[PDB]
Amino acid sequence: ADTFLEHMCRLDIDSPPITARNTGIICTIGPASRSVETLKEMIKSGMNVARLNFSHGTHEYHAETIKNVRTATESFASDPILYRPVAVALDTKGPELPAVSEKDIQDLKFGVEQDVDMVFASFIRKASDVHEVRKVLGEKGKNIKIISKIENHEGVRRFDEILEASDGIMVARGDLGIEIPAEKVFLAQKMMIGRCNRAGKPVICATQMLESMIKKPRPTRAEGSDVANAVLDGADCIMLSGETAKGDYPLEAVRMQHLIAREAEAAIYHLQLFEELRRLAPITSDPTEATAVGAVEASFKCCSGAIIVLTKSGRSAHQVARYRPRAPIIAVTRNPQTARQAHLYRGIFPVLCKDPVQEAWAEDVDLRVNFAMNVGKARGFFKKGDVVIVLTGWRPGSGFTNTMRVVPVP
Amino acid sequence: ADTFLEHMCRLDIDSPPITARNTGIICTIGPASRSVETLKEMIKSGMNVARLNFSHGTHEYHAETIKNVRTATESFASDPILYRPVAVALDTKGPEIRTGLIKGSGTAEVELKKGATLKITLDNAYMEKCDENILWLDYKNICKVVEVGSKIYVDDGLISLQVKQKGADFLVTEVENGGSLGSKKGVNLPGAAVDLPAVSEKDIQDLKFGVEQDVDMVFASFIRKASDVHEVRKVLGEKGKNIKIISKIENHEGVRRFDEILEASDGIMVARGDLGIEIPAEKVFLAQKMMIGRCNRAGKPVICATQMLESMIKKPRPTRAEGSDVANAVLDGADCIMLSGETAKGDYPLEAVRMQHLIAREAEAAIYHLQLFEELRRLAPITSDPTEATAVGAVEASFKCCSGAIIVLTKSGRSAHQVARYRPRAPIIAVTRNPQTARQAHLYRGIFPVLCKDPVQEAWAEDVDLRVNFAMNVGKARGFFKKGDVVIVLTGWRPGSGFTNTMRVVPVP
Amino acid sequence: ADTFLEHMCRLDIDSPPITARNTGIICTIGPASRSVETLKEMIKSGMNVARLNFSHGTHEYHAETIKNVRTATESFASDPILYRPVAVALDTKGPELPAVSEKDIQDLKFGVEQDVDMVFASFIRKASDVHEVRKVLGEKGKNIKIISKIENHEGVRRFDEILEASDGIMVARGDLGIEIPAEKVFLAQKMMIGRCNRAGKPVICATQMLESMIKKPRPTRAEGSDVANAVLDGADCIMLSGETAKGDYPLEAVRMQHLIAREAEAAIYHLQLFEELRRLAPITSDPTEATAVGAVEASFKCCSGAIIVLTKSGRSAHQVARYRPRAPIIAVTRNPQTARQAHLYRGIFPVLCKDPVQEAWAEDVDLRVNFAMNVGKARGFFKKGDVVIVLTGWRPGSGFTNTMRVVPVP
Amino acid sequence: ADTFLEHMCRLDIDSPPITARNTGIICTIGPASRSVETLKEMIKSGMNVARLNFSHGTHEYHAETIKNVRTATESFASDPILYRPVAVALDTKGPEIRTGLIKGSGTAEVELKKGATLKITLDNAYMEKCDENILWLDYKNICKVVEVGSKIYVDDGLISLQVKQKGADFLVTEVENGGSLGSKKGVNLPGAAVDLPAVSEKDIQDLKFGVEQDVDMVFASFIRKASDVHEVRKVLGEKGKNIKIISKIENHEGVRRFDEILEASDGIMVARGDLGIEIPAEKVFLAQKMMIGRCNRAGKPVICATQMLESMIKKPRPTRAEGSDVANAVLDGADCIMLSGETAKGDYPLEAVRMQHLIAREAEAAIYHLQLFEELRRLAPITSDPTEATAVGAVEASFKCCSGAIIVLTKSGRSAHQVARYRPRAPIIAVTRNPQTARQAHLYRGIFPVLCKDPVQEAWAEDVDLRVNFAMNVGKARGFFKKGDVVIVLTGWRPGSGFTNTMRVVPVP
Ligand SMILES: N[C@@H](Cc1ccccc1)C(=O)O
Ligand SMILES: N[C@@H](Cc1ccccc1)C(=O)O
Ligand SMILES: N[C@@H](Cc1ccccc1)C(=O)O
Ligand SMILES: N[C@@H](Cc1ccccc1)C(=O)O
Ligand SMILES: [K+]
Ligand SMILES: [K+]
Ligand SMILES: [K+]
Ligand SMILES: [K+]
């Protein structure tokens, strides 16, 4: 469809969703979803990130939840083609005042010891709050991603400085609804998602998603519409709260979130996002940035099934994700943390390569690429005769991901 | 802003809304909003259309409501610069199923609990003895159209039942979703072949009454196909031929047959709550976006209805969710938003109108007008009709010479509607001497109708200048523009002209 | 054709020119072309402007040439549908030094007395030279158009100030070839034509056009290519010199110029010219300028046969011509001078309405429009059922041409 | 500059050319330019291709010219960073008609005057007795293909005759355009069905000689249709299969059948002067623009030839008109410009090469590169061929990270040609070990070929790095870029790769 309007006119409620669900699903784990058996089913149904709410519970309790999450996750490790990484997120209590309380310091230190992937930092009002959280995590927690939660007016007013200091953003709509009038929160949500998309940083929408599923096996029309519109605004991930933490239908909530998010993909008009993001980006001569733009460009032309990115830290894959290709970004990494953290970005499908490093660099690249091809075929992103883009460095120890290759799927 | 993304990035919740609210507000009038004094305040606060729900009330009652609406409306007629036309809409009963009266004395509500049994009866002895065990309803054929396993929804989806056993004139059900059952509530039978007619005997009488009362539009309930629309058209007849028919899409068949319904109707109402019963929750937002899109493409008005500001029945302010849902209907492309119980029977009818106005006005800052137009221009079929070429040219000019308004001199409204299809940012000031045309124009996004009551000058060019000067005064007073801005003026050429084919670029003096 | 490249690829030398010749033809009148009988044939064959070279001849001699031009021109006046206005141009001797010599002053005064339409001012080096010519023409000659001839390096270096002071420009390629190297004159030509197009002022290419036709009935391949390329650069008019003044085939020269210019129209890609001219124009709220842009825009959409402009001074038609529509601009005027001067602009087909003024303004407009419709049908610009754009003012005595009308051809 | 118009407005005759000359220069070698010392100077001054005209001379003579060209070319081989490849082109005689020898002793020229009679004879007694009354020519069938009223042109259109009477073996004509008639001049019969074969007995021998001499390309004369091209291809055979065939379009039939000729050929030469005889003057500029356009769209080389700098046969500087005509051929999209008598037999062969270089270099300032590419990208068919996608991506990147060059490692040249089709601003440094590939690359606008003479490294990645480093040194020395600039590098992935499908963004060390 050559216009957004025609894209809307062609939507059909009777035809099933042909496209993959490209947004992350974050689920809050509590008494209802804590057991290894429930977590297994939640992972199969689409959970990408387990969130632990440190407003409640002891460290002993959370250590057991984390252990259960990992037991459930690694139960699928025996098939590396189908294995999905699952991230762990620590959501701080925060001030209920200083940015980091005595309790938050202890909780953050515990997160470092437990090897969590990301921190959702509560009640962030300004940049210096983010830097205080960074300082507590320290040298040992330096690769842990900090997602600043915008929960009040000051957070919204000072958004630009908070965004620049953070690794990502969580929009807490319910908390914003208390301090900001109802007729304005939807504008704040749209503003913040937009600015995050422009900056290439993850944005999560949270609170008041599928709350009615705490008691019911299906959500309301309004809730489906609200979740869908967060996806269409440009959210990278959607987070579920009590629905998965303590409700009666945690597994049904994950499945419904998956269905809604997958339906919303049919309303996304991908070409416009990219053309605007390409024009708004500053003119640069950084090799990686030029290669990322070129890859997304090629992914729209030679109607590509995927952009395969070989990445150690995830950074190269994130640079591609900023431009919002339609094609999935298969991020191949040997770093387990990188694979878990990648779920924060819309359209990144991380895969953890567990094979050992080959001495000949070109053979090692070919092995990781072949692994990505098998994963893509199995997930139905592409098949034999399709073409994909492959991004790598040139030589072992390259700082740039500056090599782009157009490759037919064998 | 040259990109949609930058348009979103520049949104600021602290800066007040610089732009006008361009969508229509339709309010349902009932016991809470019926009086001349309340209506006056609702009109000042932004009500453009009064909706009368003929599911309830006698013709005598509705005649008095209509009279009160007109008394309130004409109380502002002494200042023709500030006078706002107010339309009247008749919303038909249609093929409804309803429950009976709650039993006994005391509170007129009973708690139905999940897992509990409930017998549905058609025995008229129980018509006014509804309770936790027995529920009467008025659809006699219900046992022929429903099976074991069928779902039955009561009171706009509040309560749900599953049929466990059929009988001759009864059904034993189990309550799936509990709630308070009141008296005379609406019943939906999803996936059931309900044999009730499109226009009942009662609907015929109601439609004839609407013609006699000179209503501006009809909201036709439960439209399933084009022939239902044509039956409504036939009843309105020659005498009601200028009354606009808005088809309500309330079920799956309505959505499946949307194209034929749209082509037969003057416009569409999307009833989201009713659609939520028959269609899964994960799909209704797609149906809403599809239908609004197709209406925008066809140049026909689309109204979003149900589940707008329902919490304001009891509270002076809406929830964050409701604000977000209303706003998104506006951003999808809705021409109007309709309020139901919030204005009809709730405790804060005036606050509901004001909040709807605030939400809709805030949503305008998120609308990216240039994209809508560029796409609507490309999707329109290549034509040599003078009026269509002039309408496109006017909207084009309204984006270039950053225009404060497109002024359209129109008798029937049609010329102004053709401009509105292209979705200019600038307001369309539709100047007309026809009072009905001025009322009906509120159905279209971005049309600000003004009723010129001055007599016709013999020299045509002087008459045009007089109507344009009237539009200029109205625009200055509403803050659309001021001295030094430029406006587009569309007219015919000569008094007999069939086309609105003349465009004029005019500085505001 | 949606691209310039495809426009070139579709050119067909075997199909005849479907489009009108939109550039003006200026012919130098001398001993070979001076007679009433030859002028008649030159006018029928396409001459729009008669140029008189005041380097030679007495005032008596030139008065007779002017009289012969007018006798020939008015011989077609009995049919006002087919009558073509013919302009008279005085080309000064100039310095062969002050801008205006004693001789030039006398020649310019004679031009005012003879009611010439335009002056081609020789050897213009700077703006003050143009203002001296303006001062000599004075109040009585204030509507006479001054075309500055750029004949040397200083003229090119100071082009912007000369252009701003002049009504139009003549590029004298042969004279430029003496003072500027041959490998650079083509750049000067392209630069000057471009700047004139951007400013909305007429530009004429002169010298070394069809010189071989002084002795031969047909031009060379090279000369055809050179004339054609001046048209494709954006020239409004092409001027012939000795070919028509003193050569053996003056009538054949006019006809060949017409054929070359008409062939060149097939290579003009009109949509690009307009889209660029629209973007480069400064953002304004002048009603006439907005209406002119809108008219040209509409002329590309409702595939218009013409833009009809009712104009007293010509200015409204010139403002439309700046945007380079494909459709011919039929400029209807009662002012005989306006009709003659309009030939300086590419794409303007002037028509002189000789009917008396109707008292009712709307009827007078309708009469002039009907006249334009008959002229257009007769010239084959359009026929019954086509649609045209009509531009007018609103009341009698309107300063703006701010009214645009889409009109089917009856 | 964001518009073509502004690009023209900013042209400045006082500022020197900042950019390289990107079009090829082809020079005809004859008595004036034949010596090793002159060729050396012509190569330094910018000659990329030496053309040998086989209309005249023996094979012995041409073998010596070819040897001199190679001696001159290889004299610069001692510095492989600065060495420029020089191609050799064989231009066939084809089906030509020629006059005989001028009579008697004295001057070898006679004045034919307008209105005078001239008898054309086929009697071989008059073969060497041509004068004002009698002219012999070598086309025996001429009387069968010409009528009364037919025009006959002699010596590249200098003289024109009209046939007044036919005979068995004679034609009586009247001279229309007079001039000096010399010996053995070319004869054109416009609109006549000349039955001469596409490849004559002589052309077969000349083409076989070209294969033996290892020429790089053939300019095939008087190509009228695709089958003529295939006959030339067949004669070159298996041994001459990599020799490029450039079809010369010299008549109306060539233009009418252009598409099939283009599809059969490796490239095209537009012979404007020859076209000017058979096609009217007011149409040849359209044919030139059409043919260049179609060649650009197809990605095949197009050369403009004839009537370039002809006045430099006698003068050290060209005319304004000639400079303008050459410049406009470049701006139309020509890949190369060919010089004829200016370099073959004139008094200033070296000055002609230098002036051609200056004109072509000046014309680069008027080229608007971004438009060419954006249109060529849109007009190209949607494909999934890896090399084509990579070529487009490389040119795209060359406009963004303001690249100094696109470096392409290529064996046959094909990968570099695929990049050249998209018309990047940045030079395409085509690195090859194949000497023929390096010579043939000059046919394409914007390809700067470099011949790597270093031996192949066993490790593929090291070999790539070596060739890339060689290209970097060549680019630094030519001033295309310096340390800190960024370039695009295209290669295969692995030594067995069929595709050039790997693109690398590389800072210049
Ligand atoms: N990152 C999420 C969502 C996703 C799915 C498929 C492709 C891209 C993204 C996942 O791996 O499940
Ligand atoms: N038609 C509505 C909404 C509107 C307001 C302002 C401008 C345009 C439209 C009204 O008149 O109030
Ligand atoms: N102005 C010239 C050329 C022209 C012809 C036709 C249309 C537009 C322009 C004329 O009137 O003859
Ligand atoms: N191919 C020619 C012209 C050229 C020069 C520089 C860059 C590109 C092309 C050469 O190598 O000399
Ligand atoms: K928390
Ligand atoms: K109703
Ligand atoms: K002169
Ligand atoms: K030859």
Image (cartoon, coloured by chain):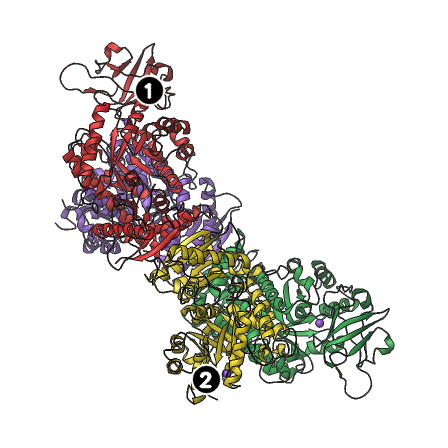
Chain colours: A purple, B red, C yellow, D green
Q: Is residue D209 above or below residue C1?
A: below
Count of marks placed on residues: 2
Residue B66, percent from left and from top: 22, 31
Residue D166, percent from left and from top: 83, 69
What's the residue type where badge 2 is placed?
A: Asp
Q: Chain of mark 2?
A: C
In the image, C181 versus A259, the foreground residue is: C181
Looking at the picture, do discs 2 and 1 lie on one chain? no
Q: Is residue B3 above or below residue D316?
A: above
Q: Nearer the viewer, mark 2 or mark 1?
A: 2
What's the residue type where badge 1 is placed?
A: Glu
Using the numbered discs, state the Cα–Cα distance from disc 2 to disc 1 in whole angstroms: 96 Å
Residue D219, percent from left and from top: 68, 68
In the image, D388 versus D482, the foreground residue is: D388
- The quadrant holding residue B296 is top left
Badge 2: few (under 14), some or many (20 or more) residues near its Cα, within 10 Å? many
Q: Is residue B51 left or right of residue C227?
A: left
Q: Is residue B138 left or right of residue C127?
A: left
Residue A373 shows in the view: yes
Q: Chain of mark 1?
A: B
Q: Which residue is mark 1?
A: B201
In the image, D119 versus B505, the foreground residue is: B505
Q: Which residue is mark 2?
A: C107
Badge 1: few (under 14), some or many (20 or more) residues near its Cα, within 10 Å? few
